[PDB]
Amino acid sequence: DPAALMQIGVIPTNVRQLMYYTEASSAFIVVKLMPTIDSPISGCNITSISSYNATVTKLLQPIGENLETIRNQLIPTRRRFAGVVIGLAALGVATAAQVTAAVALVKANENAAAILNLKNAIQKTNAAVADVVQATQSLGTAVQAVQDHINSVVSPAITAANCKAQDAIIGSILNLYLTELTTIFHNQITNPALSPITIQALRILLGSTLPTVVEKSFNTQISAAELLSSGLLTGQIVGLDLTYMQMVIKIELPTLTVQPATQIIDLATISAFINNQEVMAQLPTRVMVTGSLIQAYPASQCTITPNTVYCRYNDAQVLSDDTMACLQGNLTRCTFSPVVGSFLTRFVLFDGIVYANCRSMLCKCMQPAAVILQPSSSPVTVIDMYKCVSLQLDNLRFTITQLANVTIKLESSQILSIDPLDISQNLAAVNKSLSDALQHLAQSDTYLSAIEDKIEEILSKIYHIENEIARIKKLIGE
Amino acid sequence: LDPAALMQIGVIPTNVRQLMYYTEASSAFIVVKLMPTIDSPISGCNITSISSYNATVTKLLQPIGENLETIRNQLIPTRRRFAGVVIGLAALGVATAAQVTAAVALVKANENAAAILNLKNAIQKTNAAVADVVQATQSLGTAVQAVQDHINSVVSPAITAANCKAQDAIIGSILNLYLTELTTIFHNQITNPALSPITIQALRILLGSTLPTVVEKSFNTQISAAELLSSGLLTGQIVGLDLTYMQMVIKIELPTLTVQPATQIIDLATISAFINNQEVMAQLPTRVMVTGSLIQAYPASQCTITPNTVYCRYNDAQVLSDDTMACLQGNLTRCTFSPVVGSFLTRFVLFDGIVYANCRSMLCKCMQPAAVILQPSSSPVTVIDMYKCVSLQLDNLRFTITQLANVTYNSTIKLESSQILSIDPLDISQNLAAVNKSLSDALQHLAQSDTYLSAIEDKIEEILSKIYHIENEIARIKKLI
Amino acid sequence: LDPAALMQIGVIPTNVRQLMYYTEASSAFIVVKLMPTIDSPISGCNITSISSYNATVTKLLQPIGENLETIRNQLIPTRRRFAGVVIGLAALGVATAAQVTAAVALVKANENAAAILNLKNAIQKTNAAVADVVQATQSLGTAVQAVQDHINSVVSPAITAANCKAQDAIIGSILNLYLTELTTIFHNQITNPALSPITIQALRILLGSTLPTVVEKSFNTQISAAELLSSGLLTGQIVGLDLTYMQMVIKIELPTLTVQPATQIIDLATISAFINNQEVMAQLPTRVMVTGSLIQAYPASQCTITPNTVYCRYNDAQVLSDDTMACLQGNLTRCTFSPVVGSFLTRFVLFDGIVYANCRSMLCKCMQPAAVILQPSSSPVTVIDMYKCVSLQLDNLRFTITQLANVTYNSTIKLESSQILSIDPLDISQNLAAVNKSLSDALQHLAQSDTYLSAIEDKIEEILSKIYHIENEIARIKKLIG
Ligand SMILES: *[C@@H]1O[C@H](CO)[C@@H](O)[C@H](O)[C@H]1NC(C)=O
Ligand SMILES: *[C@@H]1O[C@H](CO)[C@@H](O)[C@H](O)[C@H]1NC(C)=O
Ligand SMILES: *[C@@H]1O[C@H](CO)[C@@H](O)[C@H](O)[C@H]1NC(C)=O
Ligand SMILES: *[C@@H]1O[C@H](CO)[C@@H](O)[C@H](O)[C@H]1NC(C)=O
Ligand SMILES: *[C@@H]1O[C@H](CO)[C@@H](O)[C@H](O)[C@H]1NC(C)=O
Ligand SMILES: *[C@@H]1O[C@H](CO)[C@@H](O)[C@H](O)[C@H]1NC(C)=O
Ligand SMILES: *[C@@H]1O[C@H](CO)[C@@H](O)[C@H](O)[C@H]1NC(C)=O
Ligand SMILES: *[C@@H]1O[C@H](CO)[C@@H](O)[C@H](O)[C@H]1NC(C)=O
Ligand SMILES: *[C@@H]1O[C@H](CO)[C@@H](O)[C@H](O)[C@H]1NC(C)=O
Ligand SMILES: *[C@@H]1O[C@H](CO)[C@@H](O)[C@H](O)[C@H]1NC(C)=O
Ligand SMILES: *[C@@H]1O[C@H](CO)[C@@H](O)[C@H](O)[C@H]1NC(C)=O
Ligand SMILES: *[C@@H]1O[C@H](CO)[C@@H](O)[C@H](O)[C@H]1NC(C)=O
């Protein structure tokens, strides 16, 4: 919490809010894998069409078989899903996510079936994008990623002359798409039908259609530029027909809300100069604060904006008692690893002010023409208008115009290395010292046990002396 | 053999696969014709983009070409018909077993590669994206040209002073786009580039829309082109090159897998658990190989995975510690738990119809017997089969449970809080510094302690003396009487 | 300096390369026309795509523009001609050196930027993939349109109400593919988007089929277009942008390389060895920098590598521990080995004709001199040169050794078993917990040995007291008797 933690060299670089998922707006798409070629054909065969159909069908066999095993067999069983999830054993061993996704799958069964009910019209229609319609109502959108390119190249008629050439252009168009499909449909998981469709997969699958579909299916105020460039869009396969080669995907757009009393701070670190060496604090690069509570929170899998971080689920990791204390101001509990600093990690601008390691890097001020030096008592030296106005950090001059407002104590036992190999070597060293301490103990024990025995002899002598003084005292005393 | 009943700790076997080794392999030769054929007549015009493309690509292939020449037409076959053993390997400088292996293969494919480049003229004259290279009614391999179909599509029937500007432009963006991708594969960084493996990813860039056709046409295997294209099975290596004709000969190889008996590759996932008053997660390898009583960490990140099989070139196993083995072998007092920030996605798992959840860290609201499932401290994880709940609700997710478990909680769980620690470097280093600090005090305390000891030795020599004199003084006083 | 007698340990030098520092960098400007030119006449027809593409590419470039403004158009130049001062940096909020460095370079190029962004119309109205930007017999750089050629092939000579739907479809997919790729480069995540660098990856997406042409045209160095495109030497930054004309001015920068006199960058590979009865591997860094007697880990993950050279903008070196340095310098008693599961691929190496192999873990069968090479426990690795074997066979691999080794240099290999341990975090923590348990017992046992020490000192104090009385009587009975 105490950002006064930048005396050490760790500077906050961002403060975003945390958004969670409340509900989701959806849309159904039918990916038409086989394009429409309705021009008459005689005395000629277009082999590429056959091959594409065969290779793609085999490629989709796992998704299909999984779909049947789950859907068309153990959950909706020759009847109509009424809301009770049954036979989840069908999934074998599944994660919470997969189980969640399976339920969503059966819940979508009725819509997927409505759309697949029109598979035939969808196939006969030549179109890159098209509204799947049933008597005055839109079920969703039907897309075919290669249709436009195909229409540009197909001959109005395919005769025995055209043949060779046509089978070639259609061939390369289909095969290129096929190849990209190969990139997305690999049979490795047990329930592939339940794997999420990423925006990258959607791009491959929908080709040049993605933009059009993105707008056509969502009415939110969010622009098509955001949906495409961010990672909010995510979909899942909800239906398949291998004969018409049509895949029904359900796309989803999250409805993000902000979680109160929670911030997600980014921490960067410049090299400090402590106890005679260039070092760098060792802390998480992204933390989450909720009052006094602090967790590590890298949103590598979340969508990040300049002022917000939207995450599917919580990815927080617990920090160590020593780490927290260090973030909460207590700098004697931090940890610094030595480093080979460079220009890029020796300084940083922070709202006009510049924080830098002037001990490791030459902070040669120009206007005041005075070379800045750094007290061995200060890890990092600040630099505002007061200390300079036109500073020059090796090959880079620039003015300074702001002013910064506002006890140090660092033990060299805080300067360690956090590297497996390095740690194991120190561990070995510590262990050898424990072994020396144990030997010292043995030596020590042996000696004390020897004194105890001499003490015994000494007592046996005191007695005899004592008794001898009692007798000699019987020739003059009682 | 790994009590899978290590599930009481929250680790669940999510997969069991067979391991497969690569006995032999089938291969085929491909000639990548880098220069498109253009037959439409040219007159009163000069397509320059073709000149540039030729120049840039020839440079980009100089390193591979030079290397290929040095090894081949220079030192390994020694420009003398190979015999059976390789000679002159010092030519490679420093090489790894994988590279030497490839070098040996290079010279072995020497004969075939020659046969193919021997037809570089015909191969180049022929306009075709894919064509069979033939000699004496035999097929030596396949000839591909990734852009041909596209070029053919755009190039006009006759190029003339009128077209020139527009034709050169389209033929240019086409060749240039290919060039860019190609420039993404051939970067000279190593000392022996001609020996670097060609991946399916590079193979795709190199062959373009031609890949599916080639894959099908090169092997007859039962495996489908879909498996071949979508798996990582296929691999290739350069074994021929003619910079003049810009034709690169490549040898593609498809393995012939075999099931190594008595071996399984198990995937291990962990849900969080509640132990000694904290939400923790067991720390173990995520993928182990098992053979008898031997367990090794087997991260097959370099292999081809199937729902039932794992196949690798060479095993990438890692040895596990005695404690970690003890743990997976069933001795839970040896496992290691790290505290974690649980979430819905990590507090339960479905295992063949029965659920396994951390009902302390999560609200397991049973719906049928309408009760809140309470998790006793002596259970880091609860099991929920039909007998405990026929209708369960887990945070907005409701489902039925109609399968019965098989009681094996015969032995109570013995777990010490010392098993709960962080396995993260930073955290480990801090702990080590604490340990060391504690030991340094002891080492100091022993040094001072070593002083109160030197004092005793003294007060003892004093006593032994005063005693020696008191004895003389007594016998003296005694002899006087 | 670095006994390669580190080879007796199975760690071998695979590459020695020179290091190179980036001195000066010759630049060049590029104007990216994000909108193609359709000159053919249009009648009664709305090419819908041109509108949509435009609305989208624009909201996409808003962040880069908005930010690029608050910086250039509002807080560094300030409605006036720059004068080498750089004020108002506070506008960047918190910014790193690389960013600040860029903000400087931005305002510095502002002049050339606006110059180009002043020939908008000439650029827009012109129809070409690659167009030289000129102003009074001078090249201000190059203007480029990634999709132009393609569009020209497609676009009909005259777009009518009959061609419409058809044309809007072809043109529309061409633009949308490009738009999609652009959606891959321009996500708004940072605070100063405009400052983020442009990679050859981003560059490729942006200029498409143009890149090879632009590159060769705007640089006259000895480096071939091939290398500039294959390596990672090229970089650029967004200097000028105009949302209305959809033109982005970019500054491509090609670095001038300068060798660091003494430094050398060595790559270390390790084969398994057989030490204290088990197969293991030495735990050293993979790439190190060596200058005289200083050694640092040098992972040039970013840098541009060549068979003989390594060029980086700034260092990425890491400090090595004393034990690691001692090991790298020949003191093998300080190295660290980890038991491993060996494989063919990691059991041997060819070093200038001579093979180095673990012949305990692998069967080193000599073919010509016909014999099986045995490796004594004392040799963690064996060296097979021509003197030992002419034709060797390492299962399936059969080759000839024609070189001789002379590195017969002798030095006793002293290796303690405490050098064989795991470097895996989980394993380290398990070991640290055991060391802790001992430290724990030692401390309790110490508590006790502190109790005796007091009790011993107690009976001593007593003895020394009884020796008082006994001493007075003997001095009394000595006088009261004379
Ligand atoms: C068309 O050609 C394909 C092979 O290219 C063949 O399998 C098919 O039988 C031919 N057409 C039919 C259905 O007869
Ligand atoms: C795919 O080929 C099969 C024959 O194997 C045929 O029944 C089916 O209609 C084809 N699908 C399409 C959409 O062409
Ligand atoms: C900061 O650490 C020191 C010792 O490491 C401790 O004495 C102090 O109490 C800690 N911070 C506070 C005041 O809680
Ligand atoms: C510590 O040293 C002893 C012998 O000196 C050894 O048995 C132990 O393995 C070493 N360290 C550990 C616990 O790894
Ligand atoms: C054809 O164009 C190339 C460059 O594009 C040029 O080098 C050559 O001179 C031209 N034709 C000739 C031989 O004049
Ligand atoms: C590529 O250019 C070279 C010389 O510039 C020429 O010899 C060669 O014929 C061209 N490509 C081919 C093999 O047609
Ligand atoms: C498990 O480990 C304990 C100590 O960690 C050991 O005493 C016990 O024998 C092991 N389990 C059994 C009974 O094999
Ligand atoms: C252990 O602590 C001692 C003093 O407390 C210190 O000298 C030593 O460097 C520490 N261990 C290591 C080598 O990190
Ligand atoms: C073309 O269509 C778009 C939307 O479909 C519309 O906004 C635009 O006004 C139309 N063309 C023009 C500029 O009139
Ligand atoms: C982009 O759209 C704007 C208005 O929507 C228009 O002024 C501009 O001409 C379009 N792009 C260009 C520069 O052609
Ligand atoms: C190598 O290490 C040993 C102990 O591990 C040490 O005694 C020796 O001095 C070191 N090498 C030399 C001779 O510097
Ligand atoms: C060492 O053991 C003691 C108790 O057995 C414990 O308090 C300490 O935390 C353990 N090691 C460390 C410093 O983590």
Image (cartoon, coloured by chain):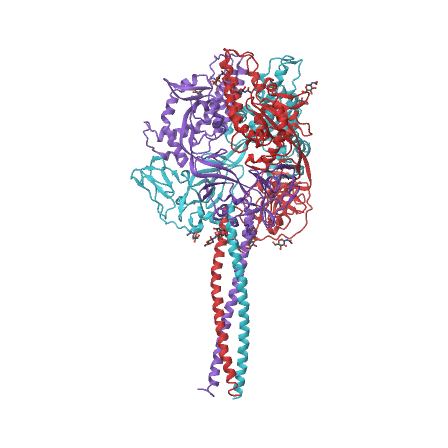
Chain colours: A purple, B cyan, C red
**Whether residue B363 can be seen here:** yes
Q: Quick check: A210 left or right of B64?
A: left
Residue B446 on image: x %, y %? 53, 62
Measured along the vertical axis of the image, is residue B440 above or below residue B165? below
Indicate the position of residue A69 as horizontal and vertical percent values: 38, 30
Instruction: Estimate the x, y position of residue B184 in percent, counting from the top left.
Output: 59, 29
Q: Please, is residue B403 above or below residue A432 in the view?
A: above
| B467 or A144, nearer to the observer | B467
Q: Quadrant of residue A234?
A: top left
Q: In this view, does C429 lie to the left or right of C232?
A: left
Q: Quadrant of ligand 11?
A: bottom right
B453 or C79: nearer the eye? C79
In the image, B69 versus C156, the foreground residue is C156
Counting the numbered discs, the total is: 0
Residue C396 place in picture, x, y as percent: 58, 38
The reply to whether residue A158 is in sight is no
